Image (cartoon, helix red, strand yellow):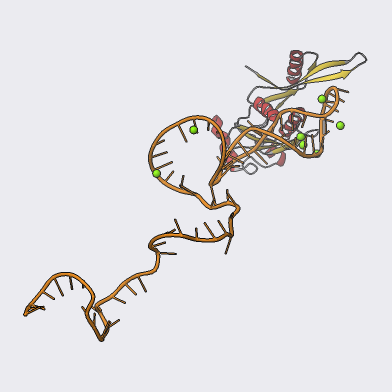
RNA sequence: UGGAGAGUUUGAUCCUGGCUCAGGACGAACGCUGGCGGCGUGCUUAACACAUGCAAGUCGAACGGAAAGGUCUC
């Protein structure tokens, strides 16, 4: 009942005297589907072994993703090694819109409503690194208010204010 | 109230970087196919030459006149 999703399976090789020694890298994203997402690279001689290593080290690389009920709090732009991923919160109707590498990471994080765009490198691993960086950049109204010293109502816009309680009644 | 990516340089990698593809549109054309209706639409090239027909006519309450019809007649 806890979601895994592998994005890229890539066969690496190391060269020796005899010939080429092959290995597999298994970038996977593990997510609960509500707010918990982790990314694991994972490497092994065998494709399922790399899958498993990636899952196991993704589940120890967790971080909370601040949402407001299906979309992110505010728009960001994560910058990876060379990956650039732009995230814009979406109206509560239009669903996830994202590229192949990003889509898995935000679906595992559990967002239902997001605009994602890969502008930098097209490598999947650096794309997910950029998206993760953007989710780190994400901030919550209730801790931005503590950061700034002012209450909730005079830091967060009235739209997201009234859009919060519509989830939990 | 709104933004998706994939393949391809290497033994393998990450960038840079082009090329290609997945979508949509036409006053369209060609291949195959094909029932109808509604509503739109049809020389994008030779402002190249045109047979043939119509597309600018009207008033007898403006006038001199009687070519035709019907009349008063012989
Ligand atoms: Mg840069
Ligand atoms: Mg690029
Ligand atoms: Mg080269
Ligand atoms: Mg090759
Ligand atoms: Mg490219
Ligand atoms: Mg036919
Ligand atoms: Mg009709």
Residue A56, percent from left and from top: 75, 16
Closest to the observer, A23 or A96: A23
Q: Residue at x 63, y 24 (%)?
A: A33
Q: Is residue B21 above or below residue B39?
A: above
Q: Is residue B1 above or below residue A10?
A: below
Q: Is residue B22 above or below residue A50?
A: below
Residue A124, percent from left and from top: 74, 28
* Picture quadrant where residue A164 is located: top right
Residue at the far right: name it: A17
Closest to the observer, B61 or A106: B61
Relative side of A90 to B59, left or right: right
* Picture quadrant where residue A101 is located: top right
Quadrant of the displayed image that contains ligand 5: top right
Residue B39, percent from left and from top: 41, 46
Is residue A19 in view? yes
Q: Residue at x 86, y 15 (%)?
A: A21
For the N terminus of chain A, the quadrant is top right
Q: Residue at x 70, y 41 (%)?
A: A149
Tell me how many marks there are: 0
* Picture quadrant where residue B49 is located: bottom right
Residue B31, percent from left and from top: 56, 33
Relative side of B67 to A32, left or right: left
Closest to the observer, B46 or A20: B46
Is residue A169 in view? no
């Amino acid at each position: 009942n806890y979601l895994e999703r592998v994005v890229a399976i890539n066969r690496v090789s190391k060269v020796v005297k005899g010939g080429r020694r092959f290995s597999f890298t298994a970038l996977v994203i593990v997510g609960d589907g509500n707010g918990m997402v982790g990314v694991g690279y994972g490497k092994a001689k065998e494709v399922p072994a790399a899958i498993a290593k990636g899952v196991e080290e993704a589940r120890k690389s967790f971080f909370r993703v601040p949402l407001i009920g299906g979309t992110i709090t505010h728009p960001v732009q994560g910058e990876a090694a060379a990956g650039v991923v732009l995230l814009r919160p979406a109206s509560p109707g239009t669903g996830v819109i994202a590229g192949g590498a990003a889509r898995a990471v935000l679906e595992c994080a559990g967002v239902h409503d997001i605009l994602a765009k890969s502008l930098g490198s097209d490598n999947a691993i650096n794309v997910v690194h950029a998206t993760v960086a953007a989710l780190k950049l994400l901030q919550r109204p209730e801790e931005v208010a503590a950061r700034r010293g002012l209450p909730i109502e005079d830091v967060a816009p009235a739209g997201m204010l009234k859009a919060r309680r519509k989830s939990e009644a």
